[PDB]
Structures are given as structure tokens and as C-alpha cells.
């Protein structure tokens, strides 16, 4: 569980065999996702 | 995907320099009209029926 | 608008023989050049196809690597340097012209040929 | 492959005979054929394109055709001037080499 209440908690997390992402919200602060492996401008 | 990094075949750390135990994975075909059958380039299309 | 050969004579076997013919006429960068060898009393065998400009080369199975060709644009000369001459290498060479940017089709007229004997 | 040809072509002045090249699969039935005539003492000269038309112009007494894996040329109005050697050329596309292969050798009598 991550929460935002100068609060800042957005690390990178490992991915294995899918993921379940849940969010409880009213103000719609999440705009999307980004994921890959390196972001080395060589791997998509 | 696209990957142009240098292969590390052996247990020796190297970067940038190419040569011994630092290989380039991308090698090119060579096509000439006088080559025999089997070395001819064959266009291949597949289908993905489900 | 024509091609003429060069003069030669008998040479020792197992040596290098220089053969050439000139080229003149139309534009040069967009016409492929064929060379073909013909033996007396039999049928001719196809020798080589050459792209001018970059000087692209291709050779048959029976002559792959054992023969060397060079080409140029400004001087307009077309050389082979034969090596490893046998009694089989006594024949007449012809230099030709093709359709242009294509190695399939009819063959434009050849020269007078060069006879080589060992 | 090897493009077998008859060793000779018999004839008399004033009649029609056919000279043919028999080839293997993917050599005659795949690509077109080229007929050539070698006059003695002269450089060889083209006489036909792909056998549906004349290249520049020849009287139509000579007719070329294909049949299966072979090619044929019927000649009529034979003269003593036209006694020469006939050759056929084709793109082989065989294993380990795909050069401009030729036929055997025939003599017109």
C-alpha cells in the first residue's frame, strides 16, 4: 500500500507473472503508467 | 527489438572496444545472383489465424 | 559505340595473363558489362557480370576466386589477370554490354575476342 | 542443368527443319531461352528475343517456340550461306551456381 497525504512515494517495483493495481480515489491524480526494463534509449 | 550492445562471450569485462571476447551480434547476409539454391534470399510471409 | 580488344600471345602455364578491352559509346554508370569465354569446337561458358561505378563483381562456380577482375570509370578499362593456366584455359574471351541495371535479358554485341593458349 | 543438344542438324537447300534444346526443370520452363547463330570467321550475332517477336528485323521464315522443358526453332528456305552452328542460352538457377548456361553443339548441313 502506497499513500499520498510534501508526501512523495513513487518507487520502481519489480514485475513478475502479472500485477494487480488498485486505487481508491476522488480527485483523479493518476494519469497513467510507464514500464520497460532499462530506459537506456535502446530498449523500448 | 533493437539491441546494438556488445556481447560479452567470456568472463572479461569490456566496453566500447570490439575484438577478443567483445563481439557484435549483428552480422549481414551477402546476396549475389551467381549464388546457388539455398543461398538465394527467399521472401517469407506467415499468418496468425486464431 | 563499339568495343575492341587487346593483343596477346602464348604464355607459360601457371602464370598471370593480363587481358583487357576498351569501352566507349553511351553513358557508363547504368549499363552492366558481361564477359564470356568461348572454346573452339564447343559451346561457350559464361565468365562474369560487372556493375560499373562501384565496380560490383560476381563470378561463376568454376571460376570463383581463381580469376581476378578490376574495373574503372574515368579511364574506362576492364582488366582480368588470369592465373593458374591449364590446357583448359586456351580459349577466346569476349567483353559485352547488357540491358542496364539488370543482369537478365538480351546480350548486346561482343568484341573480336582475345585468344589465349598455353 | 546441362542443356543437351543434338550433335548436328541435317538439311538440304529449300526446306524446313527444326533444331531444339532439351533442358531440365527450372531451366527452360522457368526462364526464357535465347537462340544464337555463329557464322564462321565472324563474331556471333543475336537473332531472337523471347520467342514472341523479332528484335530488330528478320524475315519471318524462322519461328521459335517452347514446349514444356524444351525450346525449338523451325527454319525454312535453307541456303548454303546459313550453314552455321546454333546455340541456346538460358538462366540455370541450379544448385551451387546459377550462371548463364549454354547448350551443347550442333552443325547445320
Image: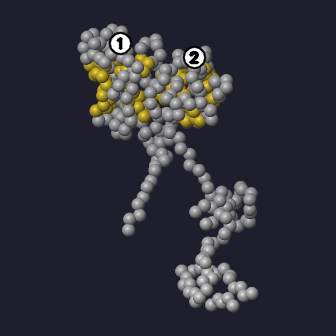
Q: Residues within 10 Å of mark 2 (few under 14, many from 20)?
A: some
Where, by quadrant of the figure, is residue C75 drawn? top right
The colour scheme used here is secondary structure
Q: Chain of mark 2?
A: C
Left or right of D17? Residue D94 is: right
Residue at the spot x=61%, y=86% of the render? A27
- Vertical placement of residue B17 versus C31, above or below: below
Left or right of B37? Residue A26 is: right
Residue at the spot x=60%, y=83% of the render? A28
Residue at the spot x=57%, y=16% of the render? C4
Which residue position holds label 2? C4
Query: Which label number is shown at residue A18?
Result: none
Image quadrant in which the N terminus of chain B is located: bottom right
Which residue position holds label 1? D82
Q: Position of residue D83 (x, y in %)?
A: 35, 13
Q: Residues within 10 Å of mark 1 (few under 14, many from 20)?
A: some
Residue at the spot x=53%, y=41% of the render? B32
Question: Are circles 1 and 2 on residues that touch, CB within 8 Å?
Answer: no
Q: Position of residue C16 (x, y in %)?
A: 64, 26
- Vertical placement of residue D55 versus D28, above or below: above
Q: Which of B38/C33 is in front?
A: C33
Amino acid at each position: 500500500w502506497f499513500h499520498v497525504i510534501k508526501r512523495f512515494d513513487n518507487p520502481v517495483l519489480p514485475f513478475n507473472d502479472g500485477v494487480y493495481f488498485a486505487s481508491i480515489e476522488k480527485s483523479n491524480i493518476i494519469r497513467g503508467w510507464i514500464f520497460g526494463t532499462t530506459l537506456d534509449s535502446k530498449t523500448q | 527489438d533493437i539491441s546494438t550492445e556488445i556481447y560479452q562471450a567470456g568472463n572479461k569485462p569490456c566496453n566500447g572496444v570490439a575484438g577478443f571476447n567483445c563481439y557484435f551480434p549483428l552480422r549481414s547476409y551477402s546476396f549475389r545472383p551467381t549464388y546457388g539454391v539455398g543461398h538465394q534470399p527467399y521472401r517469407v510471409v506467415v499468418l496468425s489465424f486464431e | 559505340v563499339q568495343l575492341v580488344q587487346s593483343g596477346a600471345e602464348v604464355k607459360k602455364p601457371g602464370a598471370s595473363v593480363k587481358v583487357s578491352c576498351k569501352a566507349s559509346g553511351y553513358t557508363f554508370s547504368s549499363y552492366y558489362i558481361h564477359w564470356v569465354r568461348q572454346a573452339p569446337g564447343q559451346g561457350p561458358e559464361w565468365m562474369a557480370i560487372i556493375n560499373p561505378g562501384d565496380g560490383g563483381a560476381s563470378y561463376a562456380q568454376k571460376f570463383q576466386g581463381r580469376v581476378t577482375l578490376t574495373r574503372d570509370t574515368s579511364t574506362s578499362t576492364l582488366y582480368m589477370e588470369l592465373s593458374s593456366l591449364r590446357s583448359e584455359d586456351t580459349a577466346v574471351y569476349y567483353c559485352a554490354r547488357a540491358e542496364g541495371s539488370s543482369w537478365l535479358g538480351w546480350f548486346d554485341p561482343w568484341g573480336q575476342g582475345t585468344l589465349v593458349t598455353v | 542443368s546441362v542443356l543437351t543438344q543434338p550433335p548436328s542438324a541435317s538439311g538440304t537447300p529449300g526446306q524446313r527443319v527444326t533444331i531444339s534444346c532439351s533442358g531440365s526443370s527450372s531451366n527452360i520452363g522457368s526462364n526464357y531461352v535465347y537462340w544464337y547463330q555463329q557464322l564462321p570467321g565472324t563474331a556471333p550475332k543475336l537473332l531472337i528475343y523471347r520467342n514472341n517477336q523479332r528484335p530488330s528485323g528478320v524475315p519471318d521464315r524462322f519461328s521459335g517456340s517452347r514446349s514444356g522443358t524444351s525450346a525449338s526453332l523451325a527454319i525454312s528456305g535453307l541456303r548454303s550461306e546459313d550453314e552455321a552452328d546454333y546455340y541456346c542460352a538460358a538462366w540455370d538457377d541450379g544448385l551451387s551456381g546459377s550462371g548463364w548456361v549454354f547448350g551443347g553443339g550442333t552443325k547445320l548441313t
